[PDB]
DNA sequence: CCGGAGCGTTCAGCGTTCGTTTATCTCCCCCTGGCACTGTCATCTCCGTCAGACCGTCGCA
């Protein structure tokens, strides 16, 4: 999606393939997010019962978790949970 | 018998002091961003109203 975001002229079939890869990447974004909904629910129930509703805490942690997945890299050899927990 | 001196009041030269601003320098407040062993489903409600109606709903006929 970064390559197709550029203004350089490429093949239209190549741009279609890049859009397909971008759609697959967005599907991966989703799949990771519904993978980690359970852990953000657990860490939100860790912080409940203090004047703020449970589902509000879950959704705010979900915002923190999409922040986490925006700032996650595979170069460091650690699991997603221990890095996501700080942002949650 | 005016004339001068002393006295009262009122103004133009420059000489200092105020009234009100301005940008720079500390101290504090306030908001966005980082954390990298792993840690991936809570929570107690609700009963000894109550009195009957109004109403839609729903499975049996």
Image (cartoon, coloured by chain):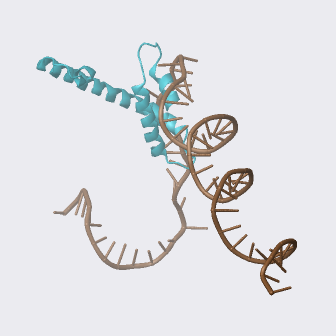
Q: Where is residue A44? Give x, y as percent.
A: 50, 38
Q: Is residue A20 left or right of residue B41?
A: left
Where does residue A46 sit, x and y in percent of width and height?
Answer: 55, 37
State the residue in front, A4 or A65: A4
Viewer-closest of A79 and B16: B16
Q: Which chain is painted in brown? A: B
- Number of labelled discs? 0
Judge whether B49 appears above or below A30 on screen: below
Q: Could you tell me residue B7's position as x and y percent?
A: 84, 76
In this rendering, position of residue B6 left or right of residue B53? right
Question: Where in the figure is residue A79, as x and y percent of width and height?
Answer: 46, 18
> Residue at point 42% right, 24% down?
A71
Q: Residue at x 32, y 30 (%)?
A: A30
Q: Chain A shown in which color?
A: cyan
Could you say which quadrant of the image residue B19 lies in? bottom right
Residue at coordinates 41% horizontally, 18% vertically from top-left? Answer: A73
Residue situated in front as seen by the camera: B40 or B31: B31
């Amino acid at each position: 999606e970064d390559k197709l975001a550029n203004s350089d002229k490429l093949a239209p079939k190549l741009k279609r393939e890049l859009e397909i890869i971008a759609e697959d990447g967005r599907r991966a974004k989703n799949h990771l997010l519904e993978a980690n909904l359970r852990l953000v629910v657990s860490l939100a129930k860790r912080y409940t019962g203090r004047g703020m509703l449970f589902l509000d805490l879950i959704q705010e942690g979900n915002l923190g978790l999409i922040r986490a997945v925006e700032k996650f890299d595979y170069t460091k050899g650690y699991k997603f949970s221990t890095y996501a927990t700080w942002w949650i």
